[PDB]
Amino acid sequence: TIYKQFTSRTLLNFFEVAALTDGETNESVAAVCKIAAKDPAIVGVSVRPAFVRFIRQELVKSAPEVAGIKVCAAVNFPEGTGTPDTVSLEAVGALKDGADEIECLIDWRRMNENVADGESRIRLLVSEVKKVVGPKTLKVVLSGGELQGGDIISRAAVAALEGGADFLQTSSGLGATHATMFTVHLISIALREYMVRERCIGIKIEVGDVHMAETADFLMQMIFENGPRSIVRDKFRVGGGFNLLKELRDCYESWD
Amino acid sequence: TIYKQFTSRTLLNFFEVAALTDGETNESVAAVCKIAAKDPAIVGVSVRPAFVRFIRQELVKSAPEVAGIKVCAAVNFPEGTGTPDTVSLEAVGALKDGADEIECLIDWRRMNENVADGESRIRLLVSEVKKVVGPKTLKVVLSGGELQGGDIISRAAVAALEGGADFLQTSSGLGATHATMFTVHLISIALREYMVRCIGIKIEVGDVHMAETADFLMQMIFENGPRSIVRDKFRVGGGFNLLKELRDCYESWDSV
Ligand SMILES: [Cl-]
Ligand SMILES: [Cl-]
Ligand SMILES: [Cl-]
Ligand SMILES: [Cl-]
């Protein structure tokens, strides 16, 4: 239908595809980047810092179109257990290698031990990394390998904002835990309240391996919580998998 | 479906409902305004100058939500037979009465008798009206419902731009014909070439249904880019029945 075609075209405009698994190779990363970069190009691709120079120095000769998508380097992945100094170094290297953005996973496990200490660590990590990112975008990933309660997510969100996050990202893309209506609601509340007490701050809804229909509901959630004006690249991104990206393209390509 | 719900929600964010017939009454205007202003409110309502004060000073006493939609006053309606001075006087009064925007119909018939003269009349009408609207938005309506050749549509568009239009509106609503893919394409080319200030396009669709209206969103993205369909530079003008179709569709989405 026209409605599915319009929804898929809109989703493509905000989409960021992940190529973050333990088993990625240059070949698997290249395949993902090629589909990301086909006109109309999506926003970007997320990879571990290892792959940035392959994409930016080598793949571009094979597939020049990849120059037209952003590369977002996933630092402190997959465990979130590095120190501010080491994660800052990862980010420095990623930016040198050609990354356009950084996504930084927090030490989410610390929130299970001592919330106050966990919040302190988030503020330090995020503020440290923001110093090396300069005016580029720093997305802070609030969840990793396990499901944590709403109160923890809310407190992680606030700490990340206080530390200087340019974007709050629901989830890493690894494991089984991704955005839910509940966590998108809590993250939206945290951001809304931070802006009232108060820069342009976004929300990235990372949906895992779900299909277009479920992804579309998150789009609707975002507009309901944060208004139509939030549906712009500086304030919104959708993170998903390769199969979801292929579904979106198949749908859009059916429009005459 | 979620796809129809998202498309409906998107259209509500662009919508300007018409209540422009000579037969309108306080009662008919109130009915349209109530559906226009229901949360989430559409952009605005188009009325003749005679109903601006009614909406802004009186209706608001029983329907306070109406303060949250814009009132766009239709000047030189319904036939485009005024002079720059008579149309300026309508605009001045409408703005005094609380109008937020002005929608000015051109003397479209003049283009059929002599193109140069028709262009000259547009440029002087539009520039004179723009002087009184000041920083508020002036939309110039290029057609009153009669089918005119492509050369005419294109030249009327350029003359309206040179005259100072802030928006190009396809058609009046009270006319027998409305926006088509053909006219939107011509208007888009004219605006693109003129740009090589912020200028918008308003696609007035008459009494068509939601599906036909959706085709225009895809046309706009393809021809003018995804960034072209934002409220600041894009509007959809349509009837009360279309507004109700959109709102009914959106209200079927579960926000809980
Ligand atoms: Cl908004
Ligand atoms: Cl559908
Ligand atoms: Cl496109
Ligand atoms: Cl908007």
Image (cartoon, coloured by chain):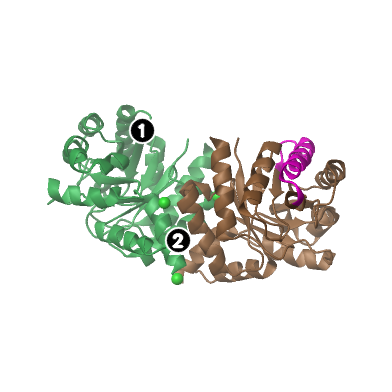
Chain colours: A green, B brown
Crowding at mark 2 (Cα within 10 Å: few <14, some 14-19, many 20+): many
Give how far across and how far down residue B65 sits, in percent.
Answer: 71, 58
Q: Earlier in the sequence, mark 1 or mark 2?
A: 2
Does residue B216 sit above or below B121 in this rendering?
A: below
Q: Residue at x 47, y 48 (%)?
A: B225
Q: Nearer the viewer, residue B137 or B220?
A: B220
Main secondary-structure element of the magenta-colored stretch? helix
Q: Which residue is mark 2?
A: A6
Residue B122 forms part of the magenta stretch: yes
Q: Chain of mark 2?
A: A
Residue B167, x across and y down, in percent: 65, 45
Q: Which residues are magenta?
A: B113-137
Secondary element type, mark 1: loop
Secondary structure, mark 2, is helix
Residue denoted by label 1: A136
A8 sits to left or right of B83: left
Q: Residue at x 68, y 60 (%)?
A: B147
Left or right: B55 as drawn, with respect to B45: right
Q: Are marks 1 and 2 in contact (CB under 8 Å)?
A: no
In the rendered structure, the residue with mark 1 lies on which chain?
A
Residue B227 location (% of width, % of height): 49, 46
Residue A172 appears anywhere in the view: no
Q: Amino acid at mark 1?
A: Lys
Q: Residue furthest front?
A: B114
Q: Nearer the viewer, residue B12 or B66?
A: B12
Pointer 1: residues within 10 angstroms few (<14), some, or many (20+)?
Answer: some
Q: CA distance from mark 1 to mark 2?
A: 30 Å
Are the residues under marks 1 and 2 on the same chain? yes
- The picture quadrant where one finds residue B236 is bottom right
> What residue lies at 80% left-to-right and 64% top-to-bottom?
B21
Q: Residue at x 32, y 35 (%)?
A: A126
